[PDB]
């Protein structure tokens, strides 16, 4: 086994040190500060993520061609795979796209309620007979 | 014969019973020989590791 | 010399204040070593700062003799000087010889018309480990200051119950071998400090069957020291007293030498204090 | 150059004749003016070594932490840099990548070390006195102001004898012993 730092050598030892430390900082730290993004502009980062999801959708139909039980991940984030492992691009992409995640998690405002007499159903509005008797 | 407040225990009187309790402590420590003396101050693994060892050695 | 001793005292004192700030970071880096091994919770303030997170990739390669004696702990044998206060009486001239005789690698130079700046410039010149000067009060001795010379700590003591070898009989001659040291009932942080300020006055590495023992008893806030010789009989070790009985207690411990008398007082005896009679090493 | 108006400033957001991305924030002339080094390539000659310390900093860290070859090595390098004077801390080892700096290596030059010993009025007037032939390191005077003085060797930098830079110093103190023609 090559799991500990005393037998493994190279950049993989440095990468497993920061990854084990990041999940330890995940369980208590605030996610707006423990997830820091390396600053890159529009056409580099937008070009980063389309080339990233092109290899992800390449991995998607490969899993569609041969049926394997793939690790199911919600579409707000991508799939953490070997491609992003050797590329070290979690610091420049930020896998959870926080603008699309915010507008999806935020529930929309409903209709402005007015008629506070009964319950809105399929049969229009239904009120109780006690409400009818107390208003008659 | 009034009473008041004092500041510190004096120098302790060296008597027979204090010395023989001290010299019994010396006798017990010599038997165990636990003297707190100042000790006189003394003084191929893996082919990737040796390659990494040689690269840092020439760089030093 | 004088620039050199001023230069290395500046680098030492800054390095003291550097590890004072580093002790919190060393304490915080202890938590990273534990949490990476056993115990998944990582505390709040250490979780955010990524500077410390990149600091530990280097700082994983890090790991007690006193730091003023750390270099010269056992690499060299301490040559030491016993002196008198000023215009010595006959009794402590005998007694400084007995302290010189109790101490291996010790010499006794008389002090008359010297000045303490010019004395410590002379022992910094020729190179010694520490100086032991003795005050007195009409024959019997009262004060004993041990001052380590390469801007080391000084420790001034007060001694009361002094009986000496020249008083009693023509008992013979002292052993003068490298002696065993018996240290007892030192527990406090100043206790471990006063151990290392005094254990280094003897030579390093005495024999396995050295025939004299110098015990230092802490029995009742007075470091009481006697010298003994011994044999190992068929059923029990017998001991016999030789050399001066002392009833000694320290009252100040300055970080500087004895030449300074304005240096950083690491510890001072407090006696006009409501809790001064309560406990020990205070 | 004309403090260009808004309709052309948005068209020209990325233009600057004075500040370019390869110029690394003008840290060359910033530490040059602070510490007063003469020529132009001397900052970068230190940057190759200060980059080489950081190169051996990262290459020490891919190694396992409890490696006995590692356990001997950076403490040997830390003592080398402490005796150099470029880094002034023995506790941390992350300082050998972070605190190793050109400003840490240029304050151990001769004319800055004058200012730390307060022998010169400014950091520039030291360069004037060094170039005129007033300053010695032991027996010999050195005229090149770009001399790194060792942490041990820092103790011995005095003025040269029989000189007018020393006579004024002793005349204020009323101490001139001119048997030694000082």
Image: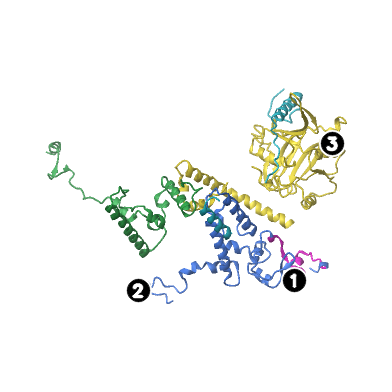
Chain colours: A green, B cyan, C yellow, D blue
Q: Earlier in the sequence, mark 1 or mark 2?
A: 2
- Is D141 left, or right, of D109 in this rendering? right
The answer to whether marks 1 and 2 sit on the same chain is: yes
Could you tell me which secondary element the residue under label 3 belongs to? Answer: loop
Q: Is residue D156 magenta?
A: yes
Give the magenta part as a residue range: D153-178
Q: Which mark is residue D164?
A: 1
Looking at the picture, how far across and down is residue C106, in whole percent?
80, 43
Residue that label 3 marks: C139
Determine whether A100 is above or below C163 in the image: below
**Chain letter of the residue carrying label 1:** D
Report crowding for label 2: few under 14, some 14 to 19, many 20 or more residues within 10 A (C-alpha): few
Q: Quadrant of the C terminus of chain D?
A: bottom right
- Distance between the alpha carbons at the discs numbered 2 and 3: 100 Å
Report crowding for label 3: few under 14, some 14 to 19, many 20 or more residues within 10 A (C-alpha): some
Q: Is residue C75 magenta?
A: no
- Distance between the alpha carbons at the discs numbered 1 and 2: 64 Å
**Chain letter of the residue carrying label 3:** C
The residue located at (40%, 71%) in the rendering is: D14
Q: Which mark is residue D110?
A: none
Determine whether D153 is above or below C185 in the image: below
């Amino acid at each position: 086994i090559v799991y500990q730092d005393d037998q493994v050598i190279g950049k993989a030892r440095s990468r497993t040190l920061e990854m084990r430390l990041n999940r330890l900082s995940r369980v208590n730290g605030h996610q707006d500060k423990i997830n820091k993004l390396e600053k890159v502009p529009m056409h580099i980062r937008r070009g980063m993520i389309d080339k990233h999801v092109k290899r992800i959708k390449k991995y998607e139909q490969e899993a569609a061609e041969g049926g394997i039980v793939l690790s199911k991940v919600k579409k707000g984030q991508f799939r953490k795979i070997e491609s992003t492992y050797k590329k070290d691009i979690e610091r420049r992409i930020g896998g959870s796209i926080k603008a699309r995640d915010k507008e999806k998690a935020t529930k929309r405002e409903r209709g402005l309620k007015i008629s506070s007499v009964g319950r809105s159903t399929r049969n229009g509005l239904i009120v109780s007979k006690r409400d009818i008797a107390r208003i008659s | 014969e009034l009473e008041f407040d004092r500041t510190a225990k004096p120098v302790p009187v060296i008597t027979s019973e204090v010395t023989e309790s001290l010299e019994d402590m010396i006798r017990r420590r010599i038997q165990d020989s636990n003297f707190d003396d100042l000790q006189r101050r003394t003084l191929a693994l893996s082919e990737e590791l040796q390659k990494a060892h040689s690269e840092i050695s020439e760089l030093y | 010399m004088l620039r050199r001793q001023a230069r290395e005292r500046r680098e030492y004192l800054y390095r003291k204040a550097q590890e004072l700030q580093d002790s919190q970071l060393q304490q915080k880096r202890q938590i990273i070593k534990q949490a990476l091994a056993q115990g998944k919770p990582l505390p709040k303030e250490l979780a955010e700062d990524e500077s410390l997170q990149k600091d530990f990739r280097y700082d994983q390669s890090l790991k007690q003799v006193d730091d003023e004696y750390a270099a010269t702990s056992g690499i060299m044998d301490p040559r030491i000087i016993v002196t008198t206060s000023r215009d010595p009486s006959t009794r402590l001239s005998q007694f400084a010889k007995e302290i010189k005789l109790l101490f291996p690698n010790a010499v006794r130079l008389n002090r008359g018309n010297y000045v303490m700046p010019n004395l410590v410039d002379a022992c910094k010149k020729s190179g010694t480990t520490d100086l032991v000067v003795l005050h007195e009060h009409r024959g019997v001795p009262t004060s004993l200051t041990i001052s380590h010379f390469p801007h080391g700590p000084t420790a001034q003591f007060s001694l009361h119950n002094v009986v000496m070898r020249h008083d009693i009989i023509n008992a013979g001659n002292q052993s003068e071998v490298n002696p065993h040291l018996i240290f007892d009932n030192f527990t406090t942080a100043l206790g471990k400090r006063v151990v290392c300020i005094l254990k280094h006055l003897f030579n390093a590495g005495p024999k396995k069957d050295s025939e004299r023992v110098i015990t230092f008893a802490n029995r009742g806030d007075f470091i009481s020291v006697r010298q003994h010789v011994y044999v190992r009989t068929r059923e029990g070790v017998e001991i016999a007293e030789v050399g001066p009985r002392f009833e000694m207690r320290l009252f100040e411990l300055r970080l500087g030498t004895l030449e300074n008398k304005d240096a950083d007082v690491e510890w001072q005896l407090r006696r006009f204090i409501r809790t001064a009679n309560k406990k020990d090493y205070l | 150059v004309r403090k260009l108006k808004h309709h052309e400033q948005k068209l020209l957001k990325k233009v600057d004749f004075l500040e370019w991305k390869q110029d690394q924030g003008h840290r060359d002339t910033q530490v040059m003016r602070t510490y007063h080094i003469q020529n132009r390539e001397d900052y970068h000659k230190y940057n190759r070594i200060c980059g080489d310390i950081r190169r051996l900093a990262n290459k020490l860290s891919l190694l396992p932490p409890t490696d006995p070859f590692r356990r001997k090595h950076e403490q040997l390098l830390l003592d080398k840099l402490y005796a150099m004077g470029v880094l002034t801390t023995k506790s941390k080892i992350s300082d050998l990548e972070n605190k190793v700096t050109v400003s840490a290596i240029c304050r151990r030059r001769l004319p800055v070390i004058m200012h730390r010993l307060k022998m010169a009025e400014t950091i520039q007037d030291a360069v004037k006195f060094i170039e005129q032939g007033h300053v010695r390191v032991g027996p010999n005077l050195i005229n090149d102001p770009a001399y790194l003085v060792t942490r041990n060797m820092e103790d011995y930098v005095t003025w040269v004898d029989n000189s007018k830079i020393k006579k004024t110093l002793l005349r204020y103190r009323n101490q001139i012993d001119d048997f030694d023609f000082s």
